[PDB]
Amino acid sequence: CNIKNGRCEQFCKNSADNKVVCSCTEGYRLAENQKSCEPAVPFPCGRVSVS
Amino acid sequence: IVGGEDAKPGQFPWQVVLNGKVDAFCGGSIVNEKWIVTAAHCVETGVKITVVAGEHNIEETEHTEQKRNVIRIIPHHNYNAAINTYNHDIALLELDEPLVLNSYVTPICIADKEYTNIFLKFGSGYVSGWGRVFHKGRSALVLQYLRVPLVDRATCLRSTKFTITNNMFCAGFHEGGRDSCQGDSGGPHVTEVEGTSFLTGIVSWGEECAMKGKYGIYTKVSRYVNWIKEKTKLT
Ligand SMILES: *C[C@@](*)(O)[C@H](CCCNC(N)=[NH2+])NC(=O)[C@@H]1CCCN1C(=O)[C@H](N)Cc1ccccc1
Ligand SMILES: [Ca+2]
C-alpha cells in the first residue's frame, strides 16, 4: 500500500507476500479488477449525480 | 462563506441548512437517511430545530427541498467539558422521518480514522454554507463554496492566542480574503478522492473572518469517526 495506495481507488490494507487487498466505503462494491470502486446503490455517498 | 462562489444545484447534495429560532443559522451534512452531523455549538439547548436538505436558494423554491424535524440531538460527550474552548465541536441530529435520497439529497462518505486523516493531509478541501459573505455582513441566499488549503499545526498555533487542540485543524490562505464565517458552522469540510467526497472536517470557529494572519478553525473529524458510526447505525 506504500505507493499510490496499492493502486486502490479508496482503501488499501497489506495482506502478505507484499500483496494488496483493496476495499471500498459503504454503498460501493469492489470492481472485478479488484482495485476500483463501483456504485452498488442508486445514490452512493460522496458523488455528484445531478449531471 | 467569504470570497467563495455560488454552488450549482446539487453540487453539494450532502449539504443541509439548519433553521430554528434563527433562520439558516448553521449548516450540516448528511450521514444517512436519518442522521445529520453538525457543530455542537449550533445546537446547545433543547430548542426546536428544522433541517432542509436539497436546499440551494433559501428565499426561492427549487422543488428539491426536503424539510425534516429534529427529534434527538447528541452533542459529543466531551463538548463543553471545558468552557468556551469549542473542543469537540461536533453533534448529531436524528430526523423524524427519513430523507429520500436523490441527486440533490446524498450522504457524504465517512472513512475510518486512518484514511480520514490521510485524506485531510491531501491538503485541500471544500467548505460550503449560507453564512456571511462579508465579515459582519450579509448572509448568502445562494449556497456558497470555497476551496481551502490545509495549514500546518505550527503556523496554526502562532496565528491565535486561543488554544488549538489536537481535535482541531486550521485551513485558509496566508494572505487572507477567503474563509468560512458566521452561519457556516456545522458545514462540511470535504476532500474529493477521485470523484468521491469524504468528510474531513466541520466548520467550528475563528477570529473575525478572512483576515490575513488568521485561519478558519475546523473540527478534526478523523477523531470522531468511530463515534459517528456508532451513534448513527440504521436498524
Ligand atoms: C457557530 C458558527 O457559525 C461559527 C463559525 C465561525 C467560523 N469563523 C471563521 N473565521 N472561519 N462559530 C462560532 O461562532 C464560534 C462559537 C461561538 C463563538 N465562535 C467564534 O468563532 C468566535 N469568533 C470566537 C471568539 C474570538 C475572539 C473573541 C471572542 C470569541
Ligand atoms: Ca430553496
Image: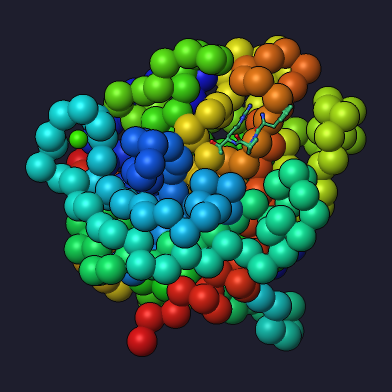
Image location of residue B131, percent across then percent down: 45, 28
Q: As displayed, is residue B142 above or below residue B225? A: above
Q: As displayed, is residue B15 above or below residue B9? A: below
Q: Is residue B19 left or right of residue B93?
A: left
Asked whether the viewer can see residue B54, the reply is yes
Q: Quadrant of the C terminus of chain B?
A: bottom left
Q: Is residue B230 left or right of residue B84?
A: left
Q: As displayed, is residue B38 above or below residue B2? A: below
In terms of image quarters, where does ligand 2 lie? top left
**Residue at (55% x, 53% y) in the render:** B44
Q: Is residue A27 left or right of residue B173?
A: left
Image location of residue B109, percent across then percent down: 46, 60
**Residue at (52% x, 55% y) in the render:** B45
**Residue at (83% x, 25% y) in the render:** B159
Image location of residue B26, percent across then percent down: 45, 40
So how many labels did they put on this image?
0
**Residue at (47% x, 64% y) in the render:** B73
The image's colouring method is rainbow
Image location of residue B200, percent across then percent down: 59, 51
Asked whether the viewer can see residue A8, the reply is no
